[PDB]
Amino acid sequence: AFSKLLFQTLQVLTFILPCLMIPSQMLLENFSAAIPGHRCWTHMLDNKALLTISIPPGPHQCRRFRQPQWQLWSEADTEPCVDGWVYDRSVFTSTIVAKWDLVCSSQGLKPLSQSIFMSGILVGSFIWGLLSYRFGRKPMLSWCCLQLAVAGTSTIFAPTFVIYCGLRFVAAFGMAGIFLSSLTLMVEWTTTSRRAVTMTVVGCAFSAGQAALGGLAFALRDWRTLQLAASVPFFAISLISWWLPESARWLIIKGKPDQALQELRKVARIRSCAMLVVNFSLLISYYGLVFDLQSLGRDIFLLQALFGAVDFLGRATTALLLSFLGRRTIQAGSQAMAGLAILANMLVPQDLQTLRVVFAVLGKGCFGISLTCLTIYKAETADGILHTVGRLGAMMGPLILMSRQALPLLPPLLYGVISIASSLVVLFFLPE
Ligand SMILES: C[C@]12CC[C@H](OS(=O)(=O)O)CC1=CC[C@@H]1[C@@H]2CC[C@]2(C)C(=O)CC[C@@H]12
Image: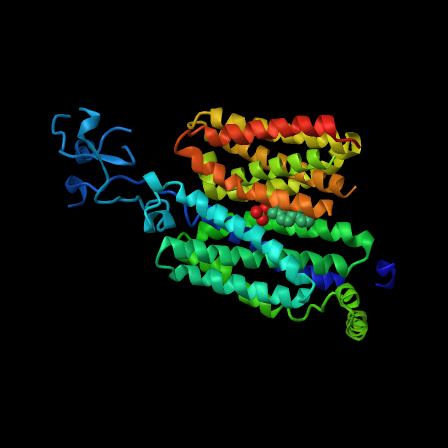
């Protein structure tokens, strides 16, 4: 009935801005932490032929000859870089991976930074939920926008990796409160019919945001400038999040009808197990793909933009596909297709870059088709549990990438096989 009792155009807009800058802040470490060509610092090179004698074949990116082989050997003439590394600055002027030597034995620290962020989202989305009964949606949006801004601008002045990772947890903690408050305010200040559409617009804004990261990165190579450009813009959103009025529904349930009466006046003046397995799988493979842009194709800038774009195309195709097929076949088929695409990429040769990029973009699009279909199917307690499982999956997606050291193919094989397995679960244990 509250839909009946019930500024929407303006509100969604005051929200397109945070939604356009959120993907940049989550998927920033694909460009700020990119891995540049690295080699051992050798006395013969930093104090073309000199490269060979100083550094063995693989130029190996982790070890160097103790004594130069003017003979050009045994693995015994190799020593780990005791003196450090010399990173290439041709493509990436500055990356965190170069600042805190996140290479070789530490190559897993980059995927962990991306999972500390994701955990910071889970722990945050949980806490902000508890504090939701006590504090309002608008104050929480405004604070969480400032928290993200302060912490995000602050990371540029972080002296050690621990502090960087810690200040990315705080930024993610804040972003969780932004996701919650934004969605909750928009849903609750619109009638139930327009609830869907509004969500489609928010989803499109996120897709444009992913695309825009590729562009922002193409312009701002320095990691410090990229972090400021993806964090500072939040201070403004915090100041422009004041006009948005507090959720009337919250006020009434809270107990304050007089305050609720004022805002409305102003606006006017203006199965479970199968589901969990699918939601975990989609997001443990999605996040794996979106956090591993460099392993997919060599051009990361094009790839991020294309990923953001293939989401819009997918949304639009989804409808026609659903016009003929069903919410179950589409989901399973799309998931299977995404897994197959991830498997194809690992197999496709490095030389054929266009093919590798095409398969990755097909994978991202297909994950988008499955995540759209799942949402419709999901709604048609449980939602909260699923989201908690989905967030856990997104925190174990960037973590499987830590295993690349041991088995390079482990990451793509796991994303592929898990996706294909969920495809079967959707097909057998989900109705229409
Ligand atoms: C799933 C996706 C789009 C991709 C984003 O991935 S990201 O990490 O690059 O921001 C995350 C993201 C966050 C919110 C999601 C959105 C897709 C559309 C969703 C499911 C709705 O209808 C309501 C909430 C929306």
